[PDB]
Amino acid sequence: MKPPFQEALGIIQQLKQHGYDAYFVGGAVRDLLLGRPIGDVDIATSALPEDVMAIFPKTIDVGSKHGTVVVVHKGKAYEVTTFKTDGSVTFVRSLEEDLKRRDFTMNAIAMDEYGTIIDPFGGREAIRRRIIRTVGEAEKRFREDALRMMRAVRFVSELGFALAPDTEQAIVQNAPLLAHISVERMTMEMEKLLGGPFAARALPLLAETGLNAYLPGLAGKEKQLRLAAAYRWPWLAAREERWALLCHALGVQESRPFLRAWKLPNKVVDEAGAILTALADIPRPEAWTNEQLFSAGLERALSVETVRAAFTGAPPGPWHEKLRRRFASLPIKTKGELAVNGKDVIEWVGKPAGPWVKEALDAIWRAVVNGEVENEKERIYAWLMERNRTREKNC
Amino acid sequence: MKPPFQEALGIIQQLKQHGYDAYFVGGAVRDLLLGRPIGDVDIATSALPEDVMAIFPKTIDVGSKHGTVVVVHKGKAYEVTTFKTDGSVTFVRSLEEDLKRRDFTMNAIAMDEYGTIIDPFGGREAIRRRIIRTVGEAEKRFREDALRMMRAVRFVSELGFALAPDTEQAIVQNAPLLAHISVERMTMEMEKLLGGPFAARALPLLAETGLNAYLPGLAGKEKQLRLAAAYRWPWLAAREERWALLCHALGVQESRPFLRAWKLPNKVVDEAGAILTALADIPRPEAWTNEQLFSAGLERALSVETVRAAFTGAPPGPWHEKLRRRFASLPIKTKGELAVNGKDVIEWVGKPAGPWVKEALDAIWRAVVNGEVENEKERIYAWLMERNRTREKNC
Ligand SMILES: [Mg+2]
Ligand SMILES: [Mg+2]
């Protein structure tokens, strides 16, 4: 009885005492059998959502409409679910009828309070063999929910399982059905597929199956995806960096339109381009300039080099260290630190408040950062003065 | 800085460090200022749902669509909410614009990381004066959501605040608007209103305001409600017992149709009847009979006597003690304990399996429970035998 379940045992135990019968189902089970670290433990029971909210003090209705209720037990969230058969939804009392609705064998295992594995569908073999197989007719399933084909590729990314001959086949055959699923639900899948320690072979597959050309911006990029294999995906730390590379490997032009089609939140789509851009502008890690670095701000700067590593093959280490070094040598790290404010430049150059002011400060920092003049009021003054009569000798 | 908030401080603290600005808003605040034990601490912020799910490890999307996200911090659930103006919903950055959307003054208070109360709407005075006042035009508010009038009466139940002259007035005027709100949402409100330490005066009000005659089964019972005042509501322990009494005080006939209209879950509407029934059947606490008790099974039995107390004025104490005493003297406490099963009566009276069997066993327990015959196989046998030739001397 590994600690993940140990704690959550209570929930089962309690639901059983009130005469209900419940099981650990789900990834948690697979993850145990497979020997991955165990993430969320999930419980399913014959107890109806209400009965669940009656027995446990802290409850959190998430969707009692489809039989799910989150139960805060001993300071951890647990997803409790009333057995169901995907039609509205129908509640039953048969564990077996519930698992039979699950997506792929390796998911439809279950384990009881005593630790006794209940694999009625071969999950257990699927996991030994490291294979993704559909629970029932690979075809029929995909018809009910096309997104199921998405996840299949995803799982390949997160687990390094291989598709099943029949499963894989079916996908290609029913690929089109995808254009019916909301973009949203497509994003999240693609999102996980990209952090896969196997993404390196997930993306290719995405093309070798029909699935390509029904996903936003991935029209006919077949070639590009397969080539993607080489990219060192796994070192991508964060979301932006991920999408960043997704582009650069699809030889994408304008970042903005594309990433937006995937209905990603703005901040991402912006910071995505940010890097992509900075990446195109600086082609070599030696060439980062006090300016560009200052502009891009440490975080991004590093994220660039990493995206870059993800492509070159070169490890960031040395760069990341160097960047972090310089960044603390920049005699200013944000504009707010500038010794000298816009109203200082006005009272100084006897000129009315305008657009010329931007340009001014915009050249005072670029001059502080580049170590031309100190970041002290007095000195920036002379500096600006003696530079303005120079623009009278130049024209 | 009282412990309930002390712990949740972390959340604010972290959201501020990422440049967002958040506050304890809600009942928590009211409860502090009022001096009640503090229930759920609620946080609202300018950080958008996503930013919230980015910063905290364990998140639980409940409804990011309306700006709410549950954040499990240090082993407790906290309802975090992006500031909003009730239109779909519009997110802002002004705390003030958020509180301005809250139902009643006493709710629209807020407190900052340093413990500095922000009452921009008189909540703080409302709490001193112990009054329920609408945030803005009592009329306009009720038009947006009629249920707001419900809560108003509820709060009276939970708090013992009085309605505001203008608030109260408005309710009667816009009473009708209620029939537009889903029954579901009406039940929950009624539910809380019944557990009120001031329910005793909440139900009356419910009638003195239009609000009566738009709520299920509460058509023209005006009289009944006001009289309700006398009932010792507050000793009601559980849900059934509550509804039980709600009936008995409205002089309700058939429990089943009524309670159902309030879309209460079956188990309740059954156990409600259960008591209401056993209550009509046994009019005095001395009269419980081994049979009846055995039938109703300790729990309900007590629940009867309490519901009764809630009405008579007599304290349960002595009865609840006496019931609990007998119930362990009943020589059986369920039918499952019966020494003798139905297949025993068949191989015994050489007759084919039928309906006469029920009637048999159904008189063997009734005879065990009443202490006529032991609950041993042998002895029940003779007893059954020697009683069956008696049904030959009788006709
Ligand atoms: Mg968990
Ligand atoms: Mg809480």
Image: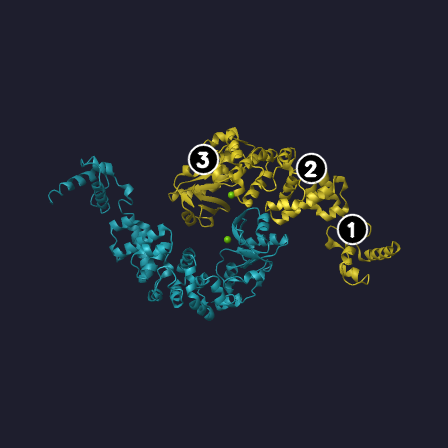
Chain colours: A cyan, B yellow
Query: In the picture provided, is B271 more to the left or to the right than A305?
Result: right
Q: What amino acid type should be assigned to the residue bearing mark 1? A: Arg
Q: What amino acid type should be assigned to the residue bearing mark 3? A: Gly
Location of mark 1 (residue):
B366
Number of numbered discs visible in the structure rendering: 3
Where is residue B80 drawn, in percent x and y?
46, 44
Query: In the picture provided, is B193 more to the left or to the right than A377?
Result: right
Q: What amino acid type should be assigned to the residue bearing mark 2? A: Ala
Q: Residue at x 33, y 59 (%)?
A: A247
Q: Is residue A314 above or below residue B101?
A: below
Which of A381/B255 is in front? B255
Q: Are marks 2 and 3 on the same chain?
A: yes
The disc label shown at residue B115, or none: 3
Which of A352/A348 is in front? A352
Quadrant of the frame with the C terminus of chain A: top left
Residue count near mark 2 (Cα–Cα under 10 Å), binned few <14, some 14–19, many ≥20 = many
What is the distance, in whole Å, between disc 2 and disc 1 at their CAs?
Answer: 29 Å
Indicate the chain on which mark 2 is placed: B
Query: On the image, which quarter does residue A389 sit in?
Result: top left
Q: Residue at x 80, y 57 (%)?
A: B377
Q: Secondary structure at mark 3?
A: loop
What is the distance, in whole Å, between disc 2 and disc 3 at their CAs?
Answer: 45 Å
Q: Are marks 2 and 1 on the same chain?
A: yes
Where is residue A294 drawn, in percent x and y?
27, 48
Which of B392/A271 is in front? B392
Q: Is residue A320 visible?
A: no
**Mark 2–mark 3 contact, CB under 8 Å?**
no
Location of mark 2 (residue):
B309
